[PDB]
């Protein structure tokens, strides 16, 4: 593989996101940056903070240029304020290029930096339409493609229990098995896609597909869980509960309020159903589906101290938008963000967490009519 030096360039915690090393300024200042396909701003801590091991020191960078404008970014969980500017940026374990990119220097924040997360910034990989202050602030990837010959495409292999790979400018065939199935990027703001069908253990949830995408369905490496619209979430939980009747769990478990732990190496994965999401294909009336295992939607909680107990939290929750395909979904696959051809590809990951009975899968093609009517106008 020609992209071998980019393999395993991501690190992280089982629910605190994946980050890549990025070198900023001159002389070099390397920091750990979160890879987020759900946002579009490149920002780094630039002032002391109890949860920051290190930060960007603008005064020490001779190539830093203050844009003399402030920026504020409120996320679904947390927010920060900073100063806009530009500086030289490189990804040591990424493409062999250096570009001058917009960079937000975070000077104040609220519930942003986590105690012992190891990351000091965030790399928004989505489009300009959702960038702050507005769409005039060119996102990092856009600068990369405009300033260099690096192809307009990147792929993510997020491996769960953490590490992974972000391949920029191409596809690394060693990171997946089987074929890559593509779904259209509906609009270029978030990485919006269209879900046309949902099954629990092969059983169709039988809801109007418009409910699956009400508002918008997206692929977001920045969100941990698989988030579903309220009406869809309720139906899905009812079905998952029925399919896992071998054992009973408290209501709060399905609501993510309570956790359930099992003796080390005794989690009854076989009692939980597989979940399949059908995505619009590239050909008229054609779709494909991705199937995830409970090992994906049941995530391990920060262990106490190598104790003989494995605690898990239900990683499917309620969303106030359409379906948000977070890390729990992506961890089972190699995901190709083919911006050049406005499509997202899915293939079984070479690091998919499965067992001897079942495995994550990407299968097709299937015949699905009126898929267009599933999207929100
Ligand atoms: C470890 O923590 C993080 C890891 C990573 Cl990589 C990135 C971030 C920030 N990132 C999270 C993802 C978010 N995505 C959307 O905003 C997409 O649009 C949505 C709209 C509605 C909904 S809802 N209301 O229905 O749930 C959900 C999503 C963008 C911001 C994290 O936060 C830390 C503080 C830095």
Image (tube, rainbow, N blue to C red):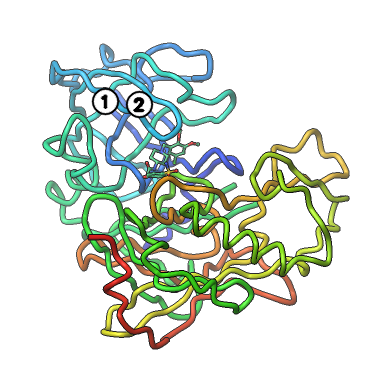
**Above or below for 282 versus 269:** below
Closer to the chain start, of discs 2 and 1, is 2
Ligand 1 picture quarter: top left
Q: Residues within 10 Å of mark 2 (few under 14, many from 20)?
A: many
User: Which residue is at 54% across, 56% downward?
Assistant: 233
**Above or below for 190 versus 115:** below
The residue closer to the viewer here, 68 or 234, is: 234
Q: Which residue is mark 2?
A: 44
Q: Quadrant of the C terminus?
A: bottom left
Marks 2/1: CA–CA distance: 6 Å
Secondary structure of the residue carrying numbered label 2 = strand
**Above or below for 300 versus 100:** below
Query: Which mark, residue 104?
Result: 1
User: Which residue is at 88% across, 50% downward?
Assistant: 263
**Above or below for 108 versus 337:** above
Q: Residue 373, how many percent across, how many down?
A: 28, 72
Q: Quadrant of the N terminus?
A: bottom left
Q: Residues within 10 Å of mark 1 (few under 14, many from 20)?
A: many
Q: As drawn, is 12 to the left or to the right of 294? A: left
Q: Are marks 2 and 1 in contact (CB under 8 Å)?
A: yes
The residue closer to the viewer here, 271 or 106, is: 271
Q: Residue 236, how many percent across, how many down?
A: 58, 62
User: Which residue is at 73% across, 41% downward?
Assistant: 258
- Quadrant of the image occupied by residue 374: bottom left
């Amino acid at each position: 593989g020609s992209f071998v030096e980019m393999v395993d360039n991501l690190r992280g915690k089982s629910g605190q996101g994946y980050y890549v090393e990025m070198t900023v300024g001159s002389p070099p200042q390397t920091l750990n940056i979160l890879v987020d396909t759900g946002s579009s701003n490149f920002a780094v801590g630039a002032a002391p903070h109890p949860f920051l091991h290190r930060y960007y020191q603008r005064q020490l960078s001779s190539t830093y240029r203050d844009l003399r404008k402030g920026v504020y970014v409120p996320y679904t969980q947390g927010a920060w304020a900073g100063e806009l500017g530009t500086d030289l940026v490189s990804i040591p374990h990424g493409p062999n290029v250096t570009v001058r990119a917009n960079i937000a220097a975070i000077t104040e924040s609220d519930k942003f930096f986590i105690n012992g997360s190891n990351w000091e910034g965030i790399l928004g990989l989505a489009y300009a339409e959702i960038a702050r202050p507005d769409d005039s602030l060119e996102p990092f990837f856009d600068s990369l493609v405009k300033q260099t010959h690096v192809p307009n495409l990147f792929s993510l292999q997020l491996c769960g229990a953490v590490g992974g790979s972000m391949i920029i400018g191409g596809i690394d065939h060693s990171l997946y098995t089987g074929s890559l199935w593509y779904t259209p990027i509906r609009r270029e703001w978030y990485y919006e896609v269209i879900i046309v069908r949902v099954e629990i253990n092969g059983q169709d949830l039988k809801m109007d597909c418009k409910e699956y995408n009400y508002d918008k369905s997206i692929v977001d490496s920045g969100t941990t869980n698989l988030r579903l619209p309220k009406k869809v979430f309720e139906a899905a939980v009812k079905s998952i509960k029925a399919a896992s009747s071998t054992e009973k769990f408290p209501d709060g478990f399905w609501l993510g309020e309570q956790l359930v732990c099992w003796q080390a190496g005794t989690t009854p994965w076989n009692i939980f159903p597989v979940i399949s999401l059908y995505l619009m294909g590239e050909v008229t009336n054609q779709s494909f589906r991705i199937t995830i295992l409970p090992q994906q939607y049941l995530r391990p909680v920060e262990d106490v101290a190598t104790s003989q107990d494995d605690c898990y939290k239900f990683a499917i929750s309620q969303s106030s938008t359409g379906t948000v395909m977070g890390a729990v979904i992506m961890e089972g696959f190699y995901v190709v963000f083919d911006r050049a051809r406005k499509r997202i590809g899915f293939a079984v990951s070479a690091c998919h967490v499965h067992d001897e009975f079942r495995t994550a899968a990407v299968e097709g093609p299937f015949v699905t009519l009126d898929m267009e009517d599933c999207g929100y106008n």
